[PDB]
Image (cartoon, coloured by chain):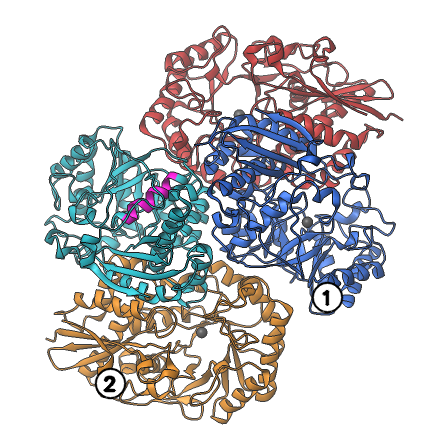
Chain colours: A orange, B cyan, C blue, D red
Amino acid sequence: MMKITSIEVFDCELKKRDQTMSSYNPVLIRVNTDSGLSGIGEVGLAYGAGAKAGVGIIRDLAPLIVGEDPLNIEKIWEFFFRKTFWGMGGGNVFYAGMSAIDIALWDIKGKYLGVPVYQLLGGKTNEKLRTYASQLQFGWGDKRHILVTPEEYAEAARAALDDGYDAIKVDPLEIDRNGDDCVFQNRNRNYSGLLLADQLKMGEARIAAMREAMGDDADIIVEIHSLLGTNSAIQFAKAIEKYRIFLYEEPIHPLNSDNMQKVSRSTTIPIATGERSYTRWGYRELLEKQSIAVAQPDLCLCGGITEGKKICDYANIYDTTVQVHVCGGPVSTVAALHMETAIPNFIIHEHHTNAMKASIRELCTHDYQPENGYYVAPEQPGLGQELNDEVVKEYLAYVIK
Amino acid sequence: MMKITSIEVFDCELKKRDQTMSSYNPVLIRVNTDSGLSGIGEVGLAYGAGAKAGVGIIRDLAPLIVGEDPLNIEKIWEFFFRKTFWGMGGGNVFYAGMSAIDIALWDIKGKYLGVPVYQLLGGKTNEKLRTYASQLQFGWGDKRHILVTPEEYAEAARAALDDGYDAIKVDPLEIDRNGDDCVFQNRNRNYSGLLLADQLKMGEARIAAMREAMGDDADIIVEIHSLLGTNSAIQFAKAIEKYRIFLYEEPIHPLNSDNMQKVSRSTTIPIATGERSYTRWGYRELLEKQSIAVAQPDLCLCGGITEGKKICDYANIYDTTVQVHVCGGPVSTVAALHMETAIPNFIIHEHHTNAMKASIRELCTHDYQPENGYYVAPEQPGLGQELNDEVVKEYLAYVIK
Amino acid sequence: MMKITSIEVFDCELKKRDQTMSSYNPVLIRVNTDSGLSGIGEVGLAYGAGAKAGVGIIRDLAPLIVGEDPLNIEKIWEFFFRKTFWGMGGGNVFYAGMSAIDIALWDIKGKYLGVPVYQLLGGKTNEKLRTYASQLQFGWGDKRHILVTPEEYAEAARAALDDGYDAIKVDPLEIDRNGDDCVFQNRNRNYSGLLLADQLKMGEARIAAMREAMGDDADIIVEIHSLLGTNSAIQFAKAIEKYRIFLYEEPIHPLNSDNMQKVSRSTTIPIATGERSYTRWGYRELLEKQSIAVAQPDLCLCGGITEGKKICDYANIYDTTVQVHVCGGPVSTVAALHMETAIPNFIIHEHHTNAMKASIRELCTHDYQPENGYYVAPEQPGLGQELNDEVVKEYLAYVIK
Amino acid sequence: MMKITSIEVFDCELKKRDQTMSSYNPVLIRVNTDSGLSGIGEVGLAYGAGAKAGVGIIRDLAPLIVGEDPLNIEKIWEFFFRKTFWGMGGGNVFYAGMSAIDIALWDIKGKYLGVPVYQLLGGKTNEKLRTYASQLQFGWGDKRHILVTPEEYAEAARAALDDGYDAIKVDPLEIDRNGDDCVFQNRNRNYSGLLLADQLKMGEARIAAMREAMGDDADIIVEIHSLLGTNSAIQFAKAIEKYRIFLYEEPIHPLNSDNMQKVSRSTTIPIATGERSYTRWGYRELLEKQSIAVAQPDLCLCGGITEGKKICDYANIYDTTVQVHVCGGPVSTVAALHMETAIPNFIIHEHHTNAMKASIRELCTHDYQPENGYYVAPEQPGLGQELNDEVVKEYLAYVIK
Ligand SMILES: [Mg+2]
Ligand SMILES: [Mg+2]
Ligand SMILES: [Mg+2]
Ligand SMILES: [Mg+2]
């Protein structure tokens, strides 16, 4: 019945509207059909080096589905995987392109069938979703800032708890002594080997101050952003084990799965990873080797809602539970909410400190925010979001038709 | 001393100048310095879905090295790997971006030191490079089109041998009975399970015709483009073993390394793969599991000349030899020539049936072609290639500065 | 262009000039060409039983390259590995001979192209190199003698920290209660089974006093010289874990790689080894079994600069960082400096307590010493050293031509 | 009561007395005592690059045992292993030094106790020793030269059979079409990857001609000299399986033990190796991985008679039988004979094609040769050999005292 007619790509250079958001660049899409139904998706490359590559991949993929039936979601996914060459040897950019399209197709399918996406994923398994305040090294607040001292870290923790959260995530090593950012700047390159006394102390003092301010019951997730190597990851874990750490996220990159297993066998802190792992194939070795307690696929990278569901289902057989990685526009948030509502192995939801920024919220028509440390799913047909056209018109980059 | 001043990106939509090359789109770069020395690179996404993403990644990566010293090649490489977020969770597009820049930096360094790149890679190890005629399902020489019948395959084989080659590569399953292309069209989807009788016979009859036309001594490489799955790959290998097959290329994709090992253990034909494997980390499980005889990294995808050399050095300890994957512009060709000249574990060089096309050759100022089945290295400083400005001006897409 | 014309071998029997240096016997070489460019190298057998074998292996290897083009460094390396019989079943002596030659060729190539060796290895990755004060069981500074009591070890530690180091290495079990040396004398043979109470107390008391003298921040590397066996290596590690040990070096010999793995799994102190491990092939089992945090190839043993770099590149994929082993003449020091400057996985640099000895220094024309705990690379073309002909004339043992 | 007084080292440059033996250079020692008893030994580096290194290692090791009691053979061995630094990371040269001294000490102990060495090794287990004619690529008997054509190979085979041998060994790939020698010349470098058709035919034609000339009952050992890599080793084995091959020797080098296992699992021809494998530690991974049917330690390399016996005893538990590697002077021959007479897991004895050369035989006072394809042990006290001082005075290089 329906056919895809066009795909709009939005290159959301947020610096155009808010200079505090200088680096951040969500990439959003809208898939239109000849029935009048449209669906929105997101390419999960809003931070780091990749936004322009993300726009480009939609230009490479979208032409293949113009004129095609949007309802054959498995077929479309499999075509991208099998018949594009790169589908069988992809990566963050290629799978992100597949993801954005997949999400927009689920949106269309939900609207067509008149139900929220979680209904098509298996129904309302989880009525409310425990949520954590994410990345407190950038503070907890409306704007806030790069935090350096343990007291500043403790204050962000107190602010998260006052806001109703009973779980927080922090990278205690990302920010160096001078307030520089080791994720994106050439600082503390020795992190990949072994930590120096001062660095160990810097990270531990921040965690220690946060635990003290939070009390014992609230949970702390320690994020590492793959800054450490196998040996420093273990060295640091042993320093922070005394603080009862809930999860250890991305203690090393996922490119060597045997090293990930080694880290997991070497600390009592359960390991989380997944934002930089894509497709069921990207999880096979992590799961088989029993290296992770929590999988963190980004639905805007891992292959979308179709593949994301499959990742969750697979993780379940290894007792691996799921926290969707969410750090982008409002589309990533609703995709995650529908997924986490339906899956039986949901553990916790990530609410990023930037998700409250006006320049991010204004990209879409609805605001979905946690209340008292919990999220609920949207209830309208499809994803329950639309692009805010008054804003996104400034960001329109390409229309594929 | 020197600083990078700008990076030009060329989106080589060949269809603008030659309609017959419609779905081929090399992506080239030029890195310019304040000394007047320039270097050229290539993003290895000339086919499949990815050219526009490849243009985009250069826009994402290039701004990070404007103003920087081009001579610190290991440092620039490591910074892209470590400090961009996605470098540690990359893929074909991200590592292609890194590759192009790296190749351009080697070009600069060679010109700066007054010697060809092979000298910087360890000197002249191989004086001449045995070369094969690549992808004969698309014909050789005069008759350039999709081949279907066994006699058409035998004719292409004779033509390659007439052209002085003593080795060919063919995918005998890519083209179906009707002349449709299974790599890029939804045809023969059952390929990934088990082959039907007609398909097995189709493939084997083409190989039979070619062996018969070539005599027993010339080598046949069977390319599969990852079209088969574990079970059908083993199935077909058994049907073609009798023809004395030199290598079996990409019998399945590389996303499940345990399946690759199983294929390797189930056929006597040695396995080759690597065009969809990136960086040392992408080879670790293939080599450790002793799954491949020959590695085929593409220097325009795998992380460039710096990482390519490292992959070759690594392969060597497993008795794995190297044929660089070459299927793009003239930049990929010279990058490969220098690599293969320097490495001790070189096996054979790939000469693609398209590398003789006018619209590819005109991209660069020099023509380097094999003679009597052998290649030799360029001898000028750097890569020994320049872009043909008269042509590439039509393709200039972005200038980063 | 050029041909190798002659190779000089210097049997540097230091006792001929300095009776205090009696055991020590650096072996140096100079490779001369018909262009007037010469390069120097070193065979890394200055201590233990091996110096005269080291002179001999150059007599065996050098004739093979007289008249050959020195720039083909990979080709020369591969020839020695492949076509001498013993290259494929070598060991400390054979690979040491290859090493010396390889280092001299890098010197030549740097000179010819007019740049320091680090530029040919990939550029200036590390602008300065953190350095440790090495082998404090023989004192530091004013006191140049065999240390016995915990208080003496504490005094050495203070001296090093006063000299501006923030890291030290000590072997706390090498010297017995009577001041005898278990590395070279038949004492404490029970070390390779299980330690006796007094021995355990002896070692731990020395570490305890050093940690107390140093404060908590400075790093301690514990050197074992392969004196312990698997079971005593673990037993001692558990006794010294409480002092926060940075690395545990050569806890056992590397001849049984499974035992090395077992030691690494049985202590939380990260393992370093590599001075008695040669070529890529000598690290394969160490790396694959994930047994080492730090690789310590000696560039004058492991196969030279060409093979050393490949070892560092390989190490990196297992998050193994590099401290080159340096305990010889000034040639070893500069080869290490160039290597450590270029590699992204450098961790720390070894400065031996004997490196300031007049009889070692006078072998060469320049001095390169650390300052405030840091080394920088030479900046001259090639290695940045020449032989001091007024001294080495008396060590000249052979001229191969 | 006895003490070692001196150690003479003989650098047997046979070219001084015989130009046809041009490069071949046995290295012999004699260990003298204050009791007037002396023992002789050999450093196993007579061919390839290493004889001068072999002379040097005796100069390094011998001083350590002057004044010591020769009878403590395990103690001396263990001291060289443990207290020399390099003993715990040695290789062919270092362990050859140990070996020569060890063999000399067994000679002494046998003379002291009035019995042949085989008595001290466990008595007369094997009364006669099946012997094969070794290295027929260099002809046999009347026609001693480099063989190229299959007819030449068949003729050497007949000659050996007419000489009373029922087993032969040949390397069918060492000599190229032009009579060049791939073991010591840069020829057929592609051997380490995959064989070309011509090379496969060349090798198989030579084996085919020998089998046809020999009949079906006589055994053929195929020697490869580690010239092949894992992939070509398997490729070649498949082509010659039809000729009923007794053993496949050194199909690849022993530096990657996982590759050796792979080769062993991929051909039905039983594998032999060991001449480039030293000490018990050098056989551990070969044995544990069940990669070898026959172990071939050289007693003049592997650690001598003490360690050789331990290697034989270890091999036994894996059903691995022993052929001692013998290609040196007459001392190597008698050490082998004694060992093989005593061990229960002897399989076959190697009789080298140059064993009857005048310049080889004249080094020693006795001549032990096979008859009708069988060797027997010497029956004199000790090894049953003395040096021929009239000849070896011309070769004396050093006397350590
Ligand atoms: Mg994260
Ligand atoms: Mg291919
Ligand atoms: Mg050491
Ligand atoms: Mg042999």
- The chain carrying label 1 is C
Q: Is residue D64 left or right of residue D311?
A: right
Up-down relation of residue B242 to residue C276 (above or below) = above
Q: Residue at x 39, y 32 (%)?
A: D190
Q: Is residue D109 left or right of residue B136?
A: right
**Label ID, residue A386:** 2
Disc 2 crowd, CA 10 A, few/some/many (<14, 14-19, 20+) = some
Q: Is residue A118 left or right of residue C286?
A: left
Disc 1 is placed on an element classified as: helix
Please state the extent of the stretch shown in magenta in the rendering: B331-341
Q: How far across and down, in percent of the image, does residue A315 sit?
A: 41, 69
- The chain carrying label 2 is A
Up-down relation of residue A243 to residue A52 (above or below) = below
Q: How far across and down, in percent of the image, does residue C136 sit?
A: 76, 55
Q: How far across and down, in percent of the image, does residue C91 sit?
A: 60, 36
Q: Are marks 1 and 2 on the same chain?
A: no
Residue B294 showing in the rendered view:
no
